[PDB]
Amino acid sequence: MNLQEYQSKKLMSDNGVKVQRFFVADTANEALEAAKRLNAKEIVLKAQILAGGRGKGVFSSGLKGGVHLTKDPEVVGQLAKQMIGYNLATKQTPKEGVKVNMVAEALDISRETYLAILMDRSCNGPVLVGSPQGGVDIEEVAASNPELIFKEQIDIIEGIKDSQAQRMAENLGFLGPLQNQAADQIKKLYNLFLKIDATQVEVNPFGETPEGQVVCFDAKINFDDNAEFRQKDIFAMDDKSENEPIENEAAKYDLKYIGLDGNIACFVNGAGLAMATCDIIFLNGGKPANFLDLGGGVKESQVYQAFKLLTADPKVEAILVNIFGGIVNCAIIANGITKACRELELKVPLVVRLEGTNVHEAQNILTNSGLPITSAVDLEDAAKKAVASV
Amino acid sequence: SYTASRKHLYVDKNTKVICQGFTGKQGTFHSQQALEYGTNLVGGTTPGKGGKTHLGLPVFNTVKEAKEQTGATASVIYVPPPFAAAAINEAIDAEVPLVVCITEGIPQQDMVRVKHRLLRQGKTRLIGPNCPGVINPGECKIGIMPGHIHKKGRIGIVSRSGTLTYEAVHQTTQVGLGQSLCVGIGGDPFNGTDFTDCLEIFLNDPATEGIILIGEIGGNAEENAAEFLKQHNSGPKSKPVVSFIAGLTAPPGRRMGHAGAIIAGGAKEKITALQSAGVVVSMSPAQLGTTIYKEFEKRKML
Ligand SMILES: Nc1nc2c(ncn2[C@@H]2O[C@H](COP(=O)(O)OP(=O)(O)NP(=O)(O)O)[C@@H](O)[C@H]2O)c(=O)[nH]1
Ligand SMILES: [Mg+2]
């Protein structure tokens, strides 16, 4: 999962991590009056999108720049109007960008360092990923000079040792008294990183102010989806516009829905097997509109909503079913497909490939149903059939 | 070292399996599948159920209780995600030679903690979590994979995917090559067994003459497996290896950070990397069986 900066920063505030004071605003006028409420010399305005590289980004409004600052509040609204509702595009967004929908006391920067905590397989647990030369150009600096990137593995049992926090702080260039304040902020970040079940906490820049303050100027937190049952309050904060409503309503019945731009709607019981079906469809000339994953669990209800959902948007002149390894006899879902197809009355072709327990008594269920349901034997067969529907 | 426990990956006629979460709905179902398939399931565990029989087999409170009394040598875990990590630790404490955690959804932090001690011991080998399990066609089936598609044969299957693993299995049985040992390592980042472990077993198993590796975009799993084959499956008696990587047609992922990019530096790179190690990458997932078959004929092995 991913939360917006302003949400990640409030979490940082409640856990001893120091950040700029800010106010949120939905409209461009509230951003102007809220910038007036802040009462601060220089103020920084940021677009909130589940994506980085905002600084060097462009805008559908042509505003050019996802982050800016100025000492004139009236310029906040002047610059806020020009992005609230527009698509902010960065080198991390899919070209089209993300529809934008924070004003904080800007602080002066005298040194930028990159800091990130994360779970990494190669390091077999938590890692402190840092660089003294942070900022937007971190990845370039990371590529041109790898030795500028310092890694410190943390023992999940012992946790963050003072000797490790001090070394990282020193490698990031925090000299003198800053070395202790930074190291402490590193220890306070790591502790938060564990508290919230985050797979990543990225602070870029991990900043040093002229007044000797170590501040986190940006907060990108990735939360472990598998930990939602223990992070109720945090997963309650995921905004009600996650990608698209087509995706959320699917997840209501735990159905993983990935959208695309195509005409065939896939329906597979396995992420890997779903991506495979999309591949082989591509090989045969089709182009999938999306795919709806089932994982392992299966219930007559899900197949009902599954079909009701895939036929939602009008860009699906056919759907492909490929269930290879359902925990229940697909002879049972075969009757869940017919039931979920005749009562829903869908006007798009329907290709089914099933393979499992008693597939013989299951395949004839579709053939003798009188419904537009064509059967397939193998994965290659299922693809060519779905493609053949134009 | 932990690698010393790789050997326990090769289940067989003799391994005596038990089931953690035995009374659970998934535990019961897949437990029956195992009994009907012939797997030597000798019982399971469920706190508060010790002393009661289930599927005609004994239920125990803890794993040691279930181990000493049955002499079990493998465990399969269906405990829900919140308590699955502990289920593993209970088996390691009981020094169960092989632990197969099927459960999907274990927090990464839990497994980082489990795996931390796992690497500090060599008694217990862990497969998964979030994997389909391991199956020795004919002799032993630990997991959820449908047994009616396997057939003891000459090809070793290692898969990071899930249900996609069954395509390679169903295709190798159809071509007549069958499977020597199929292992699913699961899709979680922190697991007990990886590609390089199963390839080591496969490269040293006589019954394993061909290899199929199944992966997908993301991570460096496939490349690490590739560099292994490049340094241990080259030269004289090199066993043919086939692979399919799902997701070549997947779209961008939409980032929110530089961290992943910095620690990296999926897609074509995984493909051409496997090719560097002499691996035959099947572009379509449907012709995995038809490919390994021909690589066998290329060097007259049928
Ligand atoms: N002087 C000053 N500059 C700031 C402040 N906040 C952000 N910036 C500038 O804005 C740049 C990028 O903004 P930021 O919100 O940190 O992140 P970003 O634009 O999403 N980039 P990235 O995804 O690489 O972290 C920083 O490198 C810094 O130069 C501030 O309070 N004061
Ligand atoms: Mg930043």
Image: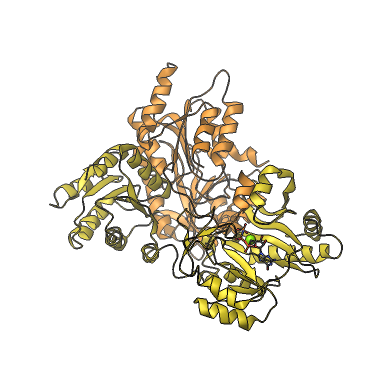
Chain colours: A yellow, B orange
Please name whichever residue, B23 or A272, is drawn nearer the observer in this view of the structure: A272
Front residue of A191 and B45: A191
Which quarter holds ligand 2? bottom right
The answer to whether residue A121 is visible is: no
Asked if B292 appears above or below A11 in the picture, the reply is above
Task: Locate residue B225 relative to residue A204 in the image: left or right.
Answer: left
Q: Which residue lies at the image location 60% right of the left edge and 70% below the top edge? A: A45
The tally of labels here is 0
Q: Residue at x 62, y 53 (%)?
A: B259
In this rendered view, identify the residue nearer to me: B246 or B31: B246
Could you tell me residue B188's position as x and y percent? 53, 50
The location of residue B257, given as percent across then percent down, is 59, 56
Q: Is residue A130 above or below residue B4?
A: below
Residue that extends furthest to the top in the rendered view of this protein: B300
Query: Residue B299, how many percent across, how many down?
Result: 45, 17
Residue A154's x, y, as percent? Answer: 72, 55
Is the residue B243 above or below the residue A270 in the image?
above
Q: Residue pushed farthest right?
A: A176
Q: From the image, which quarter does the C terminus of chain A lie in? A: top left
Identity of the residue drawn at 39% across and 45% down: A273
Write down the quadrant of residue B25 in the picture: bottom left
Locate residue A22 relative to residue A389 in the image: left or right.
right
Figure quadrant of residue A295: bottom left
In the depicted structure, whether residue A143 falls above or below residue B210: below
Q: Which residue is at 51% across, 42% downward?
A: B266
Residue A70 appears in the rendering: yes
Q: Which of A279/A122 is in front?
A: A279
